[PDB]
Length: 299
Ligand SMILES: [Mg+2]
Image 1 (cartoon, rainbow, N blue to C red):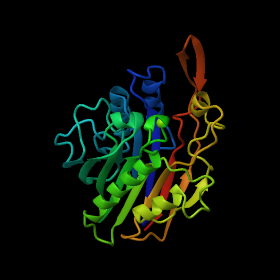
Image 2: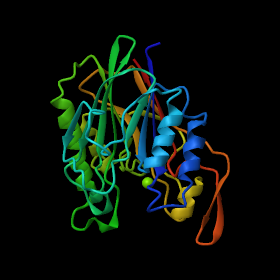
Image 3: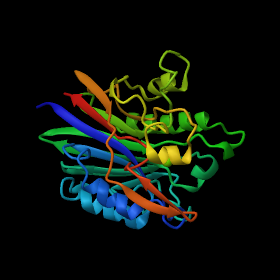
């Protein structure tokens, strides 16, 4: 059909040794059985940090998406064709990024970013590069999750670390020498806020595209990807935060140009699940604190 369906979802699967009461094991089952995550070609996952919950989620997704990477930064073995950048076996947490596909994966590279900030500096953040074979066409998908806005960053502003990380992605793409007739897609939680910024040419939002040499997609669906006013987990953690637009799937302008590319923010609600936290009982109807972004690429 000349249509690629790529989805990205930050799934809030924090390690159960630090954040034990967040329904990780249960949400792995709910997500695996959910409707919204069906019918895609490729799904990018962020925040699959918890060992068990993530194996279980990746295991539930095996039926529709049997071609899978390992989780970024969890190992450096032969599950990866190559491991690049500042990878370290001693930093406590992995990078939380995995890519799953219905189509065979010809090549799997992990890259760990050089610079980090605050708690992210204990992480192994980066990107996962995949080259995917979809009917005699090769498409390239980079899945990432950039430095978060953190108070504990210090004199290092988080925006400046993100600019660095984006340059790392772009240099990897430039020196990968990918034919300009193939599609190069970059997806994930970029931690760069579209809201109130889509009309300033010097915003961090406008710079992201310039730094990646990437085109601006068309936007449909909900107006925020992280939204304390509609989402039960984000309301619990940050009841008075304004809504943020942080998650993206975008195409490199130096390679194949789509006839169109759409980013649609979905708002699916899960079955009720409940947790006990600080002696009180809480019930949620969300899969995660982020909403998923479904991208449609017309090739
Ligand atoms: Mg988060």
